[PDB]
Image: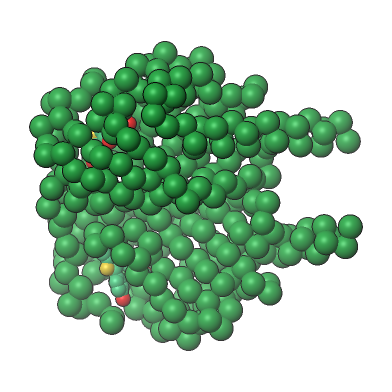
Length: 156
Length: 156
Ligand SMILES: O=C(c1cccc(O)c1)c1c(-c2ccc(O)cc2)sc2cc(O)ccc12
Ligand SMILES: O=C(c1cccc(O)c1)c1c(-c2ccc(O)cc2)sc2cc(O)ccc12
């Protein structure tokens, strides 16, 4: 059907955008915001406070990349697995990430973590990117003590 | 093609299993392990230590459900969104979960969180289930202090 053709076409184009995003590194990160719609949103959905840190708007995304290039100067996404879905405009990615972390007021460290990303598209560009990770590993990379759930009472 | 028919059939059956898993509640949780292969694995991939808590084998999954029915006595998954993928044997689920948490040696609490699940299938049953969440919300539900990354030096 004409609908299936349109959905197939959208999914193939959108997959190329996800691939490009995931392989953007170095100075090219300063232009990654051009993969978003003008009102596109990106950011980190898993933080210590329980609220997302959402960067709203293509312009603010480009401004944020200037910061992230300083505080994550050599970040790489690795082990990238891209998942298309029944929605041609919705993709998920499982990957790892790694790089130096140079966060204001903390010792320089090395950060490694597992990540899941969600990518939702509109008219050929990213409308919403969300990443999900375990913040405990970011705490460790910053030298912040991670609390330990006591396991004495739990099954082996 | 015959391959596409086989993949389409697998995906439709597997989706019904994911739906059944996500809607299993109450005493029916004691039989949820029958949705797994004999060597199937399930568990929690995001914890304070950074290592998964994997429950290995259909038999051990059924034993674990006895524990989880005591310590999460009224758990419900809500806001369930099931994502098929290009792999007919791989699904992702975005959802929320909620219920009392009655963990050994901690005050009884109420736990709410956002979750992602991965479901991989073999021969019509779950070979690997993995959940991913932000442990900071589980800490809060247990009365454990969550450290705060200092944000003074960060862009507004
Ligand atoms: O790393 C990040 C982060 C968040 C969004 C985008 C990004 O590129 C990095 C964290 C925070 C952060 C907040 C505002 C900001 O302008 C830069 C950074 S605050 C915080 C608290 C945590 O517990 C864990 C992570 C972060
Ligand atoms: O809740 C869970 C959990 C884990 C797997 C399956 C399950 O049903 C529940 C956590 C833990 C746990 C470990 C062993 C066990 O037999 C029961 C529980 S240890 C720990 C540490 C954290 O930081 C956060 C969660 C858990």
